[PDB]
Amino acid sequence: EDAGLVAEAEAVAAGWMLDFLCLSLCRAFRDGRSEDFRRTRNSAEAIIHGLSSLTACQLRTIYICQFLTRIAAGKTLDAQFENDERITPLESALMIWGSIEKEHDKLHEEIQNLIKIQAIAVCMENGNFKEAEEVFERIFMPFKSKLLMIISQKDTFHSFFQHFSYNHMMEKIKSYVNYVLSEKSSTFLMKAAAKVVESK
Amino acid sequence: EDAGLVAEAEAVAAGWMLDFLCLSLCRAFRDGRSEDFRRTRNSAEAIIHGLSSLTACQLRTIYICQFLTRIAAGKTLDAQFENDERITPLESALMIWGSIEKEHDKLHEEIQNLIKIQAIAVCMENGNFKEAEEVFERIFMPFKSKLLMIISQKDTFHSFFQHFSYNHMMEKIKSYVNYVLSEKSSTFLMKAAAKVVESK
Ligand SMILES: Cc1occc1C(=O)NCc1ccco1
Ligand SMILES: Cc1occc1C(=O)NCc1ccco1
């Protein structure tokens, strides 16, 4: 029995489980299945502990998962997270988004700008206007003066916020998720599982 | 895109991941790889949340995993666990052991008796003799009078405790784990992973 060959097989299987769980996480995010997303997120986070070295593709995969985790927590108030990071979940999604090894195309810029505005707007939606100003100061003229005046006037439903809305942010992010979903739809684990289901 | 066929494929894959993680947990337990055991335990616990209905074989698999989790925590003092269960980890392993759908052969009786004695002895090893008496009272002549006198006299290294030792309990449990390990050594995920490793 070779310990090295066993550890190698376990690393291969962890790589397969990561791809499968990413595919499942992407689908739950697209479908709005919150509980399923939470369960798959917990599984992916646990599985990646079985990998101490990741390839460039595997890093892109875990950062996509981390980004979606932050986006899904966009309207959730986590004190233990705010005290550890200093920032809100949408600001943390913005940092991940700006660092993933991916092309900065029109869709990347659109998602980036929608997250920047929604990081402020979700604080206003929750009634914390002092936090909305702190988020504005961490992220961010004539445009900056306008945005800051809007926050100061508690003008949550201003036309600018209606154009750079939460639903628009979610739709644009979902479009990106569809490319990830299609790119991974044929990974080993899901592909083998689908073959079993079709045979039944 | 059929949501039902996707959920079905995800249930198949969860069944495969459960078998793989059980195999890995069994190996880490046998090898004494504590950190690896802790990581695989966290992964298995997360993965089983993706299954709402289990077959008889799948239930046996999760109860083997739960039993090993309790045995591995045998000498660990968890207040949040003692307050939720009322009992120590080895007493919780004993309840799982007595309920798994398996044959009550010589090895089953040997493991059972070794766990009953070690549930008392690990409390004495840790210097908590009041707890050792509480454990004795929850589990449990002329033999009972002898065992209780031994606890009362803080006679931790009494010949009875040396015969029904922690090392003897671990060896007997490891022998059982070797049968589980051999029974699952050919499961889909590990088998496919091994084929990839041999091709490299
Ligand atoms: C790999 C993975 O899949 C799903 C979640 C994770 C994960 O690592 N979560 C931690 C986290 C979220 C943001 C930063 O770190
Ligand atoms: C399925 C599994 O694999 C590894 C751990 C588990 C699990 O469910 N842990 C919870 C637990 C331990 C004792 C009772 O409940």
Image: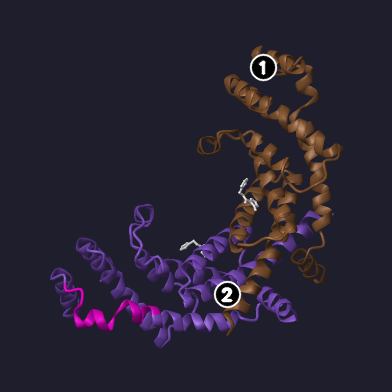
Chain colours: A purple, B brown
Taking the spot 75% from the left edge, 50% from the top edge, the residue there is: B27
Whether residue B132 sits left or right of residue A99 in the image: it is right
Tag 2, which chain? A
Q: Position of residue B60 (x, y in %)?
A: 73, 52
The nearer-to-camera label among 1 and 2 is: 1
Using the image, determine if residue B135 lies above or below residue A8: above
Determine the CA span between mark 1 and mark 2: 56 Å
Foreground of the two, A61 or A26: A26
Q: Quadrant of residue B1?
A: bottom right
Asked if the magenta segment contains residue A189, the reply would be no
Whether residue B27 sits left or right of residue A36 in the image: it is right
Q: Which residue is mark 2?
A: A23
Farthest residue toward the right? B106
Q: Position of residue A144 (x, y in %)?
A: 19, 76
Q: Position of residue B175 (x, y in %)?
A: 83, 42
Q: Residues within 10 Å of mark 2 (few under 14, many from 20)?
A: many
Foreground of the two, A184 or B82: B82
Using the image, determine if residue A140 lies above or below residue B172: below
Instruction: Write the start and end of the magenta stretch as one range.
Output: A155-170
Question: Mark 1 near ligand 2 (CB under 8 Å)?
Answer: no
> How many numbered circles does the render carry?
2
Taking the spot 63% from the left edge, 61% from the top edge, the residue there is: A51
Which amino acid type corresponds to the residue marked 2 in the rendered image? Leu
Asked if the magenta segment contains residue A157, the reply would be yes
Farthest residue toward the bottom? A106
Which amino acid type corresponds to the residue marked 1 in the rendered image? Ile
Tag 1, which chain? B
The answer to whether the residues at label 1 and label 2 have Cβ atoms under 8 Å apart is: no
Taking the spot 62% from the left edge, 59% from the top edge, the residue there is: B48
Whether residue A85 sits left or right of residue B43 in the image: it is left
Mark 1 residue element: helix
Q: Which mark is residue B151?
A: 1
